[PDB]
């Protein structure tokens, strides 16, 4: 089997991407944030505290003839921004782009934090990291990909995120028309539960490439590119007027600037992030100070190749017995 679904930015800044997902019988379609940095599939639901729902589409398990309460199971998760959610668990039929999994754990939110409430466009998350990170207790549950894998034509999924435009998540096949040149594959460590890999270096604009190992995660659920302070300082030093602002919480730059590109290495290959991809717009409405899309990972504890980086590539998440990651230009 295979599946193919369009993913769409939630706003004009590409702050996140949503992908329609069919849950239950008859289908209830929710728009979920596909997140290769976590491993829970959770949804706003009929059980979510009413004051914490503001415009989201909810899953109502009582209206699904295939829903079954997973007795005794609960879940609770936090995210990199400090947002969180928790609840109980059903199993139900879940389909993404024509690919169906029966008995998928669907984690129903009883509580969500304010940042989820405030985002009317995201009805929940669909985790695509390794199932070892799944938070269901007392019996850990498998991700959608992990459940689908044995049925797939090939044990892979691909992320093809758009810049200010829709893109695609494919399951079970590599669309050879979706990228240019060749796909360069690189080793993955699953030891921390993430798609963790090592970039071979970077360049700023038309500058020379610096060969240096940068260990980080391929994370579709993170908006920006978080890299070591040395690398980030080198980037922003090429933008007149750019500075790190403690009050704003990162690097900002004059909105009148033309940003340089940023290149990262994947083995001997190079992915070029155009400068425009690094502009996240005014820090507040009407401001001439703009927020940068490359930020320091110091204090996070890990480097994160988020959407800013991933959207510049066609990315293969290879879930073979020994997982790997593939990157191609597009
Ligand atoms: N994508 C997610 N759900 S969390 C990404 C993340 C952020 C920080 C650290 Cl330390 C690890 C992972």
Image: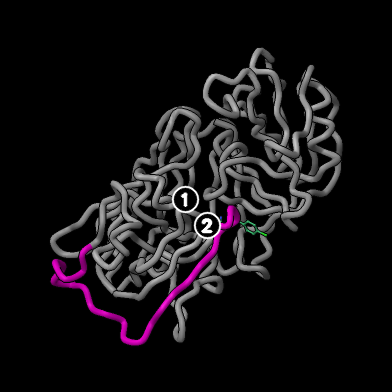
Image quarter for ligand 1 equals: bottom right
Element type at mark 1 = helix
Disc 1 vs disc 2: Cβ atoms closer than 8 Å?
yes
Residue at 38 percent across and 61 percent down: it is 152
159 vs 151: above or below = above
Judge whether residue 291 can be spotted in this image: yes
Apparent side of residue 271 relative to residue 33 in the rendered image (left or right): right
Q: Nearer the viewer, residue 276 or 81?
A: 81
Question: How far apart are the alpha carbons under marks 1 and 2?
Answer: 6 Å
Horizontally, residue 157 falls left or right of residue 278, namely: left
Q: Position of residue 172 (x, y in %)?
A: 41, 55
The one nearer the camera, 230 or 98, is 230
Is residue 35 shown above or below 16?
A: below
Name the mark on residue 115: 1
Q: Could you tell me which secondary element the residue under label 2 belongs to?
A: loop
* 167 relative to 132 in the view: left or right: left
Task: Locate the C terminus and report the quarter of the image it occupies.
Answer: top right
Residue that label 2 marks = 83
* Magenta stretch holds residue 71: yes
User: Which residues make up the magenta segment?
Assistant: 60-83
**Mark 2 Cα within 10 Å, few/some/many (few <14, many 20+)?**
few
């Amino acid at each position: 089997s295979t599946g193919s679904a369009t993913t769409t930015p939630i706003d004009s800044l590409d702050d996140a991407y949503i992908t329609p997902v069919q849950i239950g019988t008859p289908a209830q379609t929710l728009n979920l944030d596909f997140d290769t940095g976590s491993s829970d599939l959770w949804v706003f639901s009929s059980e979510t505290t009413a004051s914490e729902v503001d415009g989201q589409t909810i899953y109502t398990p009582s209206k699904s003839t295939t829903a079954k309460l997973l007795s005794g199971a609960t879940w609770s998760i936090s995210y990199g921004d400090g947002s969180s959610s928790s609840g109980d668990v059903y199993t139900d039929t879940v389909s993404v782009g024509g690919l169906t999994v029966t008995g998928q754990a669907v984690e129903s939110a009883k509580k969500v934090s304010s940042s989820f409430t405030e985002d009317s466009t995201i009805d929940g998350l669909l985790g695509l990291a390794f199932s070892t990170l799944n938070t269901v207790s007392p019996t850990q549950q498998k991700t959608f990909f992990d459940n689908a894998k044995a049925s797939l034509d090939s044990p892979v999924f691909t992320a093809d995120l758009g810049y200010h435009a829709p893109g695609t998540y494919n399951f079970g096949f590599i669309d050879t028309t979706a990228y240019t040149g060749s796909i360069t594959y690189t080793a993955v460590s699953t030891k921390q539960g993430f798609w963790e890999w090592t970039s071979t270096g970077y360049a700023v604009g038309s500058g020379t490439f610096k060969s240096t190992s940068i260990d980080g995660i391929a994370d579709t659920g993170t908006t920006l590119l978080y890299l070591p302070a040395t690398v980030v300082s080198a980037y922003w030093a090429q933008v007149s007027g750019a500075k790190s602002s403690s009050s704003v919480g990162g690097y900002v730059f004059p909105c009148s600037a033309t940003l340089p590109s940023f290149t990262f290495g994947v083995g001997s290959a190079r992915i070029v992030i155009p400068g425009d991809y690094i502009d996240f717009g005014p820090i507040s409405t009407g401001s001439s100070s703009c927020f940068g899309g490359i930020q320091s990972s110091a204090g996070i504890g890990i480097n994160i190749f988020g959407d800013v980086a991933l959207k510049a590539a066609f990315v293969v998440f290879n879930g073979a017995t020994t997982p790997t990651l593939g990157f191609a230009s597009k």
